[PDB]
Image 1 (tube, rainbow, N blue to C red):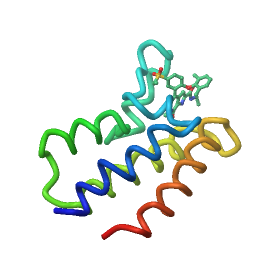
Image 2 (tube, helix red, strand yellow; image 1 turned 45 degrees about the vertical axis):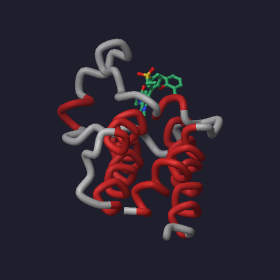
Image 3 (cartoon, rainbow, N blue to C red; image 1 turned 180 degrees about the vertical axis):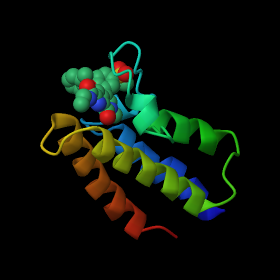
Image 4 (cartoon, helix red, strand yellow; image 1 turned 135 degrees about the horizontal axis):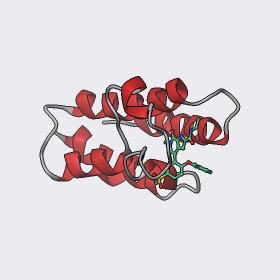
Length: 106
Ligand SMILES: CCNC(=O)c1cc2c(-c3cc(S(=O)(=O)CC)ccc3Oc3c(C)cccc3C)cn(C)c(=O)c2[nH]1
C-alpha cells in the first residue's frame, strides 16, 4: 500500500521531527514517572515509536489500522491528563499537524 509508505516517509517523519514530539516517541513509562494508575485507565497504550516499529515490521493490515494507532495516541493523552496540561497542548498541536498531513494521503 502506497498510503502505508506515505504514513512512514511523510506523516511519521513530519510528526517525529516536531518540537513537541519527544514525549510521544516512546511508551509512557508509568514506573519511572510514578503514574501507577496509567495502565489501569489507558487500556491501549500507543506512541510514535511503536507505530514506527509497526510500519517498519509489516504489522499493519492497512493504512486505517495505522491512522487508528495515531488517534489512540492522541485520545489516550486527553483521557489520562487534564485539559490545559502542557502534554495535552503538545498532543493537540501534533494532532492538528497529523490531520493536515493525512489530508494529502494518496
Ligand atoms: C497527569 C500527570 N501526567 C503526567 O505526568 C504525564 C507525563 C506524560 C508523558 C511523559 C513521558 C516521558 S517519557 O520519558 O516516559 C516518554 C518519552 C517523560 C515526560 C513526560 O511528561 C512530562 C512532560 C512532557 C513535561 C514535564 C513533565 C513530564 C512528566 C508523556 N505522555 C504522552 C503523557 O500522556 C504524560 N502524562
